[PDB]
Image (tube, rainbow, N blue to C red; front, side, top):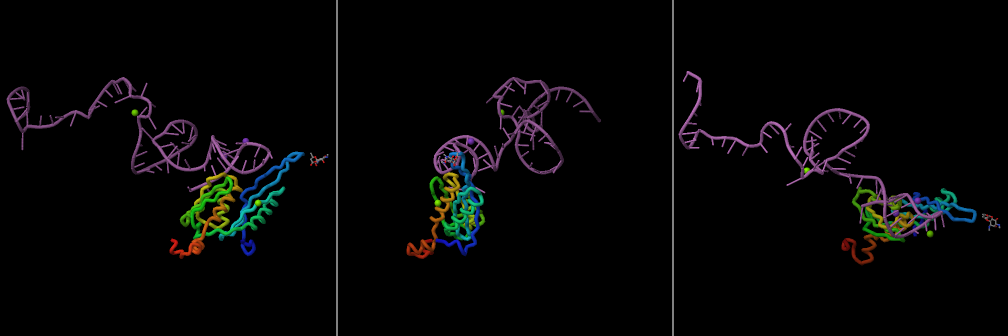
Length: 163
RNA sequence: GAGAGUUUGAUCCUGGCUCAGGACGAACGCUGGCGGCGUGCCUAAUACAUGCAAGUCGAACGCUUCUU
Ligand SMILES: CN[C@@H]1[C@H](O)[C@H](NC)[C@H]2O[C@@]3(O)C(=O)C[C@@H](C)O[C@H]3O[C@@H]2[C@H]1O
Ligand SMILES: [K+]
Ligand SMILES: [K+]
Ligand SMILES: [Mg+2]
Ligand SMILES: [Mg+2]
């Protein structure tokens, strides 16, 4: 668990989807907002908020995202190793990149990575474009990412021996 | 190793279609200052006026026309 407090979190509105519930009189229109809130230092989360008005949906989503913050391993400006994250339709593949290459990624993955604070990475989305699913798939891949120190500790060998 | 639009009242998935890039012996439209380097019948191996694109050797040979 990562406490939102003590972290200077900033948010970005990934998607604002106007959803409809059909009611006897007609259409009941609501706004569903997907938000990604991150620390630019390795912590990031995503939250969903539904409300009659766009600002309120965004605010609800922001609070949810803070609750869901997670930490991403990072070696320099890029991730430790290649990782594929799959959630539902979403399917993302993210690879380390050389320094200065930038963030090669599309749409929602861009927000997740920027907010997380990763500056250089290569990513490809092999699944659907559904923003919620791709964001979920992104965080799944990041949770798969492993630290050299943790791996070295787990396997019982020095990190130098591992590499 | 970037995506985006579009099926629905709304949603996820599947799925096609379309677009954002680059390329060219290009052509067309509008427009048009210069220079360097390059390229220019992709079609009818269709038909071709005209001129030229294969001559040279007198130290292999015998002739023949003029200059004093
Ligand atoms: C018989 N009275 C109806 C009934 O109460 C409906 N709710 C069950 C009620 O529904 C509404 O309140 C609605 O929300 C829909 C609207 C077409 O009619 C409205 O009035 C509707 C009332 O007129
Ligand atoms: K349509
Ligand atoms: K599609
Ligand atoms: Mg939830
Ligand atoms: Mg020809």
